Amino acid sequence: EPVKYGELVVLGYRKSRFALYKRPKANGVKPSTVHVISTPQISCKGQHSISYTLSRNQTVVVEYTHDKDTDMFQVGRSTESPIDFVVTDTITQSTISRFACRIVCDRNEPYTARIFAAGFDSSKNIFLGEKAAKWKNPDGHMDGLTTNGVLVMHPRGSQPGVWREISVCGDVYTLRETRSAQQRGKLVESETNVLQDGSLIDLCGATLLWRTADGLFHTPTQKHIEALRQEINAA
């Protein structure tokens, strides 16, 4: 009983193309207890945690727990243990993040893949410092954007679609004024962070092509070569 979620492919113009398979024992996490605390002078939890540091005092700490029905896959430029696919730039300095983003996959059918901005570090942490876009929504919960952000788009199946920012909790947002301003975009309550076949993900410095399991199983990505170049003409 082997199961492949799908595949990642680095668009040209540390490997080429990373496939994703349902790991034996669930990797996934999902958030729980929240702690809020002020301080004259970053902090977190010896577990999976995300830290939102609002003032020079108050800091929210969302401590993530084991999720039974999901697998996590981390992408970024770090080569430490928690990164599952190392992505280098697609050329000076270095734009991509060490822990760019997570791909969380449902372990039961139809094995949906969803993307989240930021990956946990070699310490189980995401840190969101003052100098980075954050907020609480009416839902009650905290959320933020990564400094550069993860941008996702999906084309019409004809193709070139619209680019969007992914928060650190899913939630789709319209682009910032300019790529990475502290001023975040606007919510899109009606779009999700689901990766449908042939979605594009810009990690800021590299682009990746998501491919659904059934996706590849019907069309080879070779036929989609021209469109991807016509569509990468969105930038």
Image: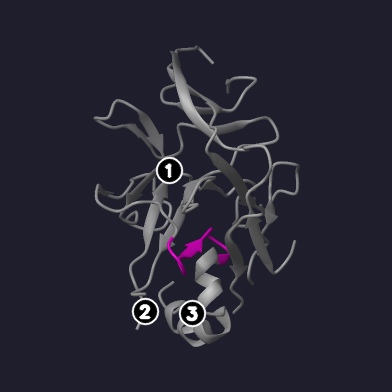
Q: Is residue 137 above or below residue 202?
A: above
Q: Is residue 93 visible?
A: no
Q: Residue at x 40, y 51 (%)?
A: 193
Q: Residue at x 45, y 39 (%)?
A: 132
Q: Is residue 199 magenta?
A: yes
Mark linked to residue 39: none
**Would you say the residues marked 2 and 1 are in contact, meaning their CB atoms lie under 8 Å apart?**
no
The residue wearing badge 2 is 159
Residue 161 in the image, given as x and y percentages of width and height: 34, 72
**Would you say the residues marked 2 and 3 are in contact, meaning their CB atoms lie under 8 Å apart?**
no
The residue wearing badge 3 is 228
Residue 19 lies left or right of residue 217; in this view the side is right
**Distance between the Cα atoms at labels 3 and 1?**
26 Å
Judge depth for marks 2 and 1 and give the one in front: 2
Which quadrant of the rendered structure holds the C terminus?
Answer: bottom left
What secondary structure is found at the residue carrying circle 2? loop
Residue 200 in the image, given as x and y percentages of width and height: 47, 66
Amino acid type for the residue under numbered disc 1: Leu
In terms of sequence position, does the residue under pointer 3 or pointer 1 come before the other? 1
Residue 146 in the image, given as x and y percentages of width and height: 48, 44
Residue 68 in the image, given as x and y percentages of width and height: 55, 33
**Would you say the residues marked 3 and 1 are in contact, meaning their CB atoms lie under 8 Å apart?**
no
The residue wearing badge 1 is 145
Amino acid type for the residue under numbered disc 2: Gln
**Distance between the Cα atoms at labels 2 and 3?**
9 Å
Camera-side residue: 56 or 14? 14
Q: Is residue 70 above or below residue 76?
A: above
> What is the magenta range?
196-208
